[PDB]
Image (cartoon, rainbow over all chains, first blue to last red; front, top):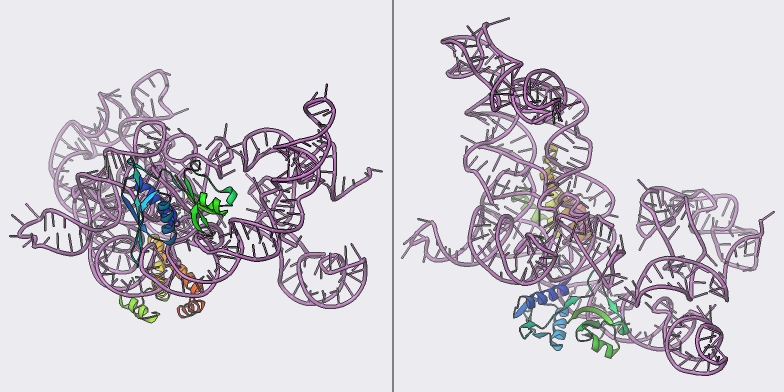
Length: 129
Length: 88
RNA sequence: UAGGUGGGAUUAGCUAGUUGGUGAGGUAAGGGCUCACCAAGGCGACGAUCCCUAGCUGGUCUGAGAGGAUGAUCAGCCACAC
RNA sequence: AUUACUGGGCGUAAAGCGCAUGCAGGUGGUUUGUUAAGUCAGAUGUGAAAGCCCGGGGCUCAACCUCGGAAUAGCAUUUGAAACUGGCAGACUAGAGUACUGUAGAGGGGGGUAGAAUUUCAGGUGUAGCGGUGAAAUGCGUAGAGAUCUGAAGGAAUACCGGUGGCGAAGGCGGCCCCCUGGACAGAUACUGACACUCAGAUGCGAAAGCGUGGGGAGCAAACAGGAUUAGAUACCCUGGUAGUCCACGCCGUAAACGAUGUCUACUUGGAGGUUGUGGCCUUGAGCCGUGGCUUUCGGAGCUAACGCGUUAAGUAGACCGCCU
């Protein structure tokens, strides 16, 4: 069964970037869209779009720079089989601060930088580098 | 094995709505009918191990649907049991 | 009271004051603490029971850390005194 | 990083249970609200002193002694946050399943039957070999073999079709016919509404040999006998030959039970095939083009110690199980 939609999102992006696909579509969800918004903010994707009302699909436009894919790493951290929650003082730095770690805080979903500045910890979704 | 007329008798009897084929009630009732019919076969055909694997999938599936419904509406579950004669 | 605190499943059942109730007694004090009586409970695969090993902790040693190992001296607690 | 939480593995180096079903467990689609158990933030209490660490201070320095801090990653109470996980109450249809109609198939169980052939037997014809091998001998044959014709009786297996075809969870399944029966797949519409995935323990199925009881016994053949070969020949070869092989009902539970590759899910260039559905076109002419299922092969990226694997992954990820050291 598919028991981790988020990891599926990340896989789809990671495999898209690997196959030099322009965009990737997947079944949308709140958290997928939230992730896609952060990834846009941080400049790792080009854009996203949620089409459909009945069964909404998400379309991440992937980003390349010098014909290498912008996303090098897209590691899921908090799996379903092992959740990972870090306090603010214990938030992961990624690629020596040059990558993000997507934290889910109780005031939304943010990069580890913004979480530290906010003095929130939360659930670590993934590392993007 | 259950043909179409016998199915339809059941699908009409246990239907929880209009042209309900898919309620636990219908599904379980059909499986119960299949299982009960097939009991004659395996009395006459004990060595039929391959067909029995298919019998036991029905037995399994019944349980799963019955565990579903009990989880949903215990009262519906209690009805269905009583109407079918299952001691689940 | 709860949580934590070795090893063994080639140790899986264990228990019958046992588990709970009632009353009495008993105690500085709650309490099967004890007895009588009533009931058949209780515990156990989140490892009871049994067997082996062992004083516990603050710490100590090692380790980038996470860990691993350990519990002289000092201090706290426990137990013991042919 | 040699027990790998951090931080390993399992095609061939050690490692995927033979296959499956499935309870507990683990995990679990989308969505609204709520709750606040997990999570996060803060406060308060506590977390002895010593030690460790950071600043000092005092011994000629140092060890040592000592002051202050930090630390004690925890726990309790409490106040907030509500993204994520959980709970609770709903909602949804993509997962999973149901109904309908078809399709292909050595899927299974039961029963019957056909033809070829072997052996035995009976009779006919016939007459000296036959059989076997590297050669030979054992053996068979004048009591008539072998050959040939006819018939009979039995048992077992189904030539051709036949296929890197098909079906099945795996083991496995092959003449034809009937009866009983499982699964898969496709099309179409309707239904249920996460009912799911995986599974410790458990349960079931599980080649061949073997075992029990009762049958059956053509052919084959462990054992065994004899003949050869040889230094020997407890073998290979030859002539025989019993259990077994077959049936019924049990038992056994194992195989290089192999893809030496757990199950489920999603994603990621292609080329050439096979097979089984379905739609369209003009069937304008066997076809061509779509769309599914299953299967074979070659290869790209990637992966891999390499060999190789390569959309049927050994690629990219997730859930769970088994297992290695």
